[PDB]
Amino acid sequence: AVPFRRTSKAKKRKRRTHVKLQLPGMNECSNCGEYRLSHHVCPECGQYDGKDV
Amino acid sequence: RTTYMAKPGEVERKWYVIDATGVSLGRLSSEVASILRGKNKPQFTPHIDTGDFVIIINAGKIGLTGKKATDKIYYRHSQYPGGLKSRTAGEMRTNNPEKLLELSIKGMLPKNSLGRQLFKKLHVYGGSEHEHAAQQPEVYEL
Amino acid sequence: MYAIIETGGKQIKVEAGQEIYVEKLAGEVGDVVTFDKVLFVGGDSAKVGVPFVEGATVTAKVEKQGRAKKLTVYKYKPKKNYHKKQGHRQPYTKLTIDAIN
Amino acid sequence: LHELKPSEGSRKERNRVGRGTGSGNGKTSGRGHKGQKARSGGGVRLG
Amino acid sequence: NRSEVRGGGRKPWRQKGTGRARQGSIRSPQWRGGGVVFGPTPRSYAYKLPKKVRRLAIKSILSSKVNEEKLVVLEGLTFDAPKTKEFAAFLKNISVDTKALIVVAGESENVELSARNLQGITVIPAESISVLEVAKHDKLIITKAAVEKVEEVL
Amino acid sequence: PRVKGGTVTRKRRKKIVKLAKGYYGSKHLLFKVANQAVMKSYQYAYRDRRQKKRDFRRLWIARINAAARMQDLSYSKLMHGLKLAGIDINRKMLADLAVNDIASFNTLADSAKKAL
Amino acid sequence: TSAKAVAKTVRIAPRKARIVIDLIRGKQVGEAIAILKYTPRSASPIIEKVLKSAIANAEHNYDLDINNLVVEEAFVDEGPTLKRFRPRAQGRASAINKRTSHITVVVSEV
RNA sequence: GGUUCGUGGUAGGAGAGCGUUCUAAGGGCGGUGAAGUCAGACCGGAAGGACUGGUGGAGCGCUUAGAAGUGAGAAUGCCG
RNA sequence: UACUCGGGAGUCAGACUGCGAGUGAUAAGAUCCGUAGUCGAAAGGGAAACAGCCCAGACCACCAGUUAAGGUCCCCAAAUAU
RNA sequence: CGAUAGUGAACCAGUACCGUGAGGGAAAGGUGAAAAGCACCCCGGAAGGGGAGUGAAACAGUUCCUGAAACCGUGUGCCUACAAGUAGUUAGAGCCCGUUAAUGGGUGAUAGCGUGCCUUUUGUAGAAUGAACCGGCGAGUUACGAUUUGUUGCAAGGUUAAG
Ligand SMILES: [K+]
Ligand SMILES: [K+]
Ligand SMILES: [Mg+2]
Ligand SMILES: [Mg+2]
Ligand SMILES: [Mg+2]
Ligand SMILES: [Mg+2]
Ligand SMILES: [Mg+2]
Ligand SMILES: [Mg+2]
Ligand SMILES: [Mg+2]
Ligand SMILES: [Mg+2]
Ligand SMILES: [Mg+2]
Ligand SMILES: [Mg+2]
Ligand SMILES: [Mg+2]
Ligand SMILES: [Mg+2]
Ligand SMILES: [Mg+2]
Ligand SMILES: [Mg+2]
Ligand SMILES: [Mg+2]
Ligand SMILES: [Mg+2]
Ligand SMILES: [Mg+2]
Ligand SMILES: [Mg+2]
Ligand SMILES: [Mg+2]
Ligand SMILES: [Mg+2]
Ligand SMILES: [Mg+2]
Ligand SMILES: [Mg+2]
Ligand SMILES: [Mg+2]
Ligand SMILES: [Mg+2]
Ligand SMILES: [Mg+2]
Ligand SMILES: [Mg+2]
Ligand SMILES: [Mg+2]
Ligand SMILES: [Mg+2]
Ligand SMILES: [Zn+2]
């Protein structure tokens, strides 16, 4: 319930291989050639599926 | 100063065939281990595999003096409680002699990364026939 | 052609033009050294010593007297507070072999 | 005064105890281990 | 020391049950703003060897100056008024040009003043002649009366 | 006068730490570990300068024997025959010949085989 | 040729920033700006302003094409800690480390 | 400078030294770059000492003596 | 080498092994004496590993040699020895 | 003594802070010769930056001379996903560099050997103790007296204390 030993730099880093976060699943609006999230409304043009909002 | 150390690929490495008929397990294995470690060659270098590749046939006719066919017992353990499984040397000679000579020679090779790599150079057959004719191997006599 | 010659309480294999290091020899730079304790000769021949070849010698030229790289010796006995430290540079003589006679 | 060289054996470097094991006067500093004599003020009367 | 440093008294924590090392004062030596353990205390270092040894020392350092040819003995030494120009000029009219100690007993009314601005130069009234004050200098400039007085003393 | 413990402490400890070069993690950085790694390496090197000579003699012997079995002698009978013949060439040279001048190795083995 | 920007003493903790930076490093600035816009983390506006500043001063000082710029190297150095306490049970307190960052972005054409 | 015998070592005895701060004297380097610090594959039988280069940007070594707040890896040490 | 005089200490928890005796149960890695040895304060080779057993005493270096205990089919150096 | 030193206090310190109270009791120094303390431009809401400029210098920019180590990271030359190993050492390939040039440097597949330091113990890798790490500070000293050794001076004499 208490550490018997201090985690070394290497073992710390070997845990931290997976804490990362991923590039977001985005792409360019067909209307504005400007990056946006798939299946989401573009915040720049305010448009979705060829239809303003 | 200056004494020869081999290099991997520096040495020719041959393919040998042995008829294991009638020879005692241990004596045959002792000759094979030295072949694989490369002590028949003066190019020997302890940290490099200079040794040869080896084939053994008629392993089901390997000799076992005494009552070893019934009383020499090989053991395995599964790392589970009561996971101990025993099998006799004679039974192994009958059914799975390849594993028998593998077990004998493994304990006679060194217990390292190298020795594990050397075990791979062994090809055992209880019969008179092998797959490795493409390598066109030579007979070795003990 | 090559030879085997005893030097410094030990034996070395030796050819002409070879640059050799051995224990300290009384001899200045440029001077010449005659090794008369030749044990073996090879090359287009073989004459075996019993122990030394009669009348065969080797000639060599002193190129440098030196002291080798600084070795540090250090001994310690744990929990007894014995430490001991020492330097060493083993003096050597550098030779160039001229010929084998 | 830049050449002063007093008599030999008139002067002698103070022993300094407890500044290493190579001095031979180190850890315990000539007192040994664990008694009344290894202590500060340790010892007894003269008689 | 730990008795003179301001504070202490409180034991900062219980002898037992804190997990901290046992302590008795915030001013103990191992502590940051704490006492010094032995350190310096005011002392006189002054010791004096026997009188005979000291007399011998003076006789010896003087004879060393003699053997080294660094005495300069002169009939007299006077100045009409204090004038470091004139004193310095004397110090070339005798090729002194180093650190020097003048010794005087005569009239010598203005010589101390005419020397005291010069750094390598010292002057004394012939009773004060010390081993140290001599050895501290290179050359020794002793007047006739001063040497006579040093003689009758020694 | 007072003596601040300046500059000598860290000079010494840097020297130790730089001798701790190449080691895992805190051994090449931190003095309390580096010092004892350095000492242990020194001790290992002391005794390896003795174990090394043994190891090379062991290898020399092995190669000689591997080379003499080809000529149908053992190392043992080879050494015996060579002492009888009286030549005091050493294991190092015998290995060098066995691995590079096998003809001359075999010449000496023949001389031994005669003296037997 | 290169142009950089630095946001010194920003209150974001360095780990929380680096976890985001590791995406940005080695990419074209339009891409990276979009990564930061659409990556929902406390650090992304910070890193976005630093990146945009690097682009701006590339343009305005060093006379460079924005449309060939990459992220040459980005990183997060540690800065001063502000030291704090939450009050904890049974009379005692436990430290808190309000950490800070020096976020640095460097920008160059190919 | 030679011959002979030796040269494991705890407590501990004996000796010779390295190094730090200061002083005195002598003699010196140092804005054409001091101490300090960083890096190095140099030196000495050891403690340790030089050299080169970078950073720094004003003081510091050497020699012989002397005096000491004299050398830390541990004290559930003290402060940061 | 011994002794004498003087300066300076540290030590007064000892351990196993072999031999001789006790207590013990002709038990104990027990305990207590005597004797000799090793450890302590001793690295090294061998007993798988191993303070205390067997051999044997490290100033330093050397990619030289002969030997001890113990060993020579393989792990593992050397006899698949007579 | 030279900012963990030296007064507790080199700075608005017996202050802040603690305590009902008596009472305890800190931490904290350095721009530059001179503010000449960054006009103006750009990102930005600001902070903070990048230029420009001042200055010998801003990797001297309002904890601002120097700026060690722990610590955190960026990048990269060599190795690493059939392997356990007080983490090194010795042998050693291959790869990569080129030095206070000397039988050089860095890495290290693989092979051999190898149970930290200290303390206390008959005996400790020790499943006994202590230390998270790094840095600083931190333990035989001074006065007076006894005794002995060495040195110096005088010598059946030697030496003065206070003054
Ligand atoms: K210190
Ligand atoms: K410098
Ligand atoms: Mg002394
Ligand atoms: Mg002593
Ligand atoms: Mg001692
Ligand atoms: Mg100690
Ligand atoms: Mg003790
Ligand atoms: Mg005791
Ligand atoms: Mg005692
Ligand atoms: Mg008090
Ligand atoms: Mg040997
Ligand atoms: Mg409460
Ligand atoms: Mg000794
Ligand atoms: Mg001290
Ligand atoms: Mg007992
Ligand atoms: Mg007994
Ligand atoms: Mg003891
Ligand atoms: Mg032993
Ligand atoms: Mg062993
Ligand atoms: Mg022990
Ligand atoms: Mg000895
Ligand atoms: Mg032999
Ligand atoms: Mg063998
Ligand atoms: Mg300071
Ligand atoms: Mg203070
Ligand atoms: Mg600063
Ligand atoms: Mg692999
Ligand atoms: Mg454990
Ligand atoms: Mg602990
Ligand atoms: Mg510490
Ligand atoms: Zn869009």
Image (spheres, coloured by chain):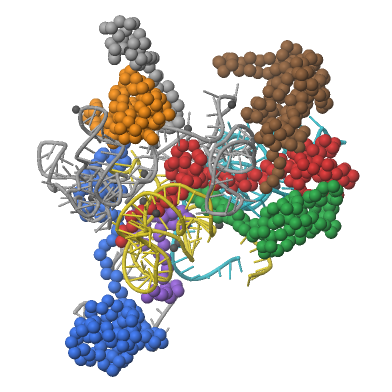
Chain colours: B brown, C green, D purple, E blue, F red, G orange, H yellow, I cyan
Q: Which residue is painted at 34% across and 33% down in the image?
A: G63
Residue F65 vertical position relative to residue H10 in the rendered view, above or below: above
Where residue G29 appears, as percent x and y from the top left, is 36, 25
Is residue E61 left or right of E121 when viewed as pictured? Answer: right
Q: Is residue C73 visible?
A: yes
| Foreground residue among E76 and E152 | E76
| Foreground residue among C35 and B122 | C35
| Foreground residue among F2 and G80 | G80
Q: Which residue is painted at 21% across and 89% down in the image?
A: E79
Residue B8 vertical position relative to residue B1 in the rendered view, above or below: above
Is residue I56 left or right of E48 when viewed as pictured? Answer: right
The quarter holding residue H63 reads bottom left
Where residue B95 appears, as percent x and y from the top left, is 73, 11
Residue F16 vertical position relative to residue F71 in the rendered view, above or below: below
Where residue F91 appears, as percent x and y from the top left, is 75, 45
Q: In which quarter of the image is ligand 4?
A: bottom left
| Foreground residue among G77 and G67 | G67
- Of the 4 image quadrants, the one containing the N terminus of chain E is bottom left
Q: Is residue G96 visible?
A: no
The quarter holding residue E82 reads bottom left
Q: Which residue is painted at 28% across and 54% down in the image?
A: E36
Is residue H24 left or right of H18 when viewed as pictured? Answer: left
Q: How many labels does the image show?
A: 0
